[PDB]
Image (cartoon, coloured by chain):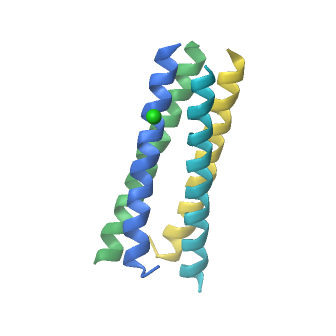
Chain colours: A cyan, B yellow, C green, D blue
Amino acid sequence: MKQIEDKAEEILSKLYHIENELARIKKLLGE
Amino acid sequence: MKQIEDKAEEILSKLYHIENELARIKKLLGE
Amino acid sequence: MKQIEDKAEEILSKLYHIENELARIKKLLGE
Amino acid sequence: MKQIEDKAEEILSKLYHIENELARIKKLLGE
Ligand SMILES: [Cl-]
Ligand SMILES: [Cl-]
């Protein structure tokens, strides 16, 4: 459970990374 | 635990957003 | 909990979708 | 529950794979 929250956090932190990599690809293609 | 269900919701919702990003990308590539 | 498993399943099913959309973009760019 | 922790692991691992896809993409775009 405290380990669950650690894994939740890693999961969110990967999910913002991915959002953000994707946002930068969309920006580039749209240039 | 509904804290854990809460987190799963928050997860999916991020994944929905990610899928919208990729729908924009795919259009910009004419898919 | 049975609802947790439902949300897990949706989460996996979005994650394979995303993997797969991404695999098809990589294929296209690499052509 | 370690079934739930198990699932979270399986989640992250998919997200790692997704990040590898996007590293290939980004290179193909010369980022
Ligand atoms: Cl939901
Ligand atoms: Cl892990």
Quarter holding the C terminus of chain C?
Answer: bottom left
Q: Quadrant of residue B7?
A: top right
State the image coordinates of residue B24 (x, y, percent, origin top left): 58, 67
Q: Residue furthest left?
A: C31
Q: Residue at x 45, y 38 (%)?
A: C13
Look at 43% across and 63% down and name the residue there.
D22
- Residue at position x 46%, y 16% from top? D3
Q: Quadrant of residue A17?
A: bottom right
Decide if residue D18 is on the left or right side of residue A30: left
Q: Is residue D6 above or below residue B31?
A: above
The tally of labels here is 0
Q: Position of residue B10 (x, y in %)?
A: 68, 37
Residue C12 locus on image (x, y percent): 46, 36
Name above or below for residue B28 compared with residue B22.
below
Quarter of the image that includes the N terminus of chain C: top right
Residue A14's x, y, as percent? 55, 49
Residue B12's place in the image compared with D2, above or below, is below
Residue at screen point 58% across, 46% down: B15
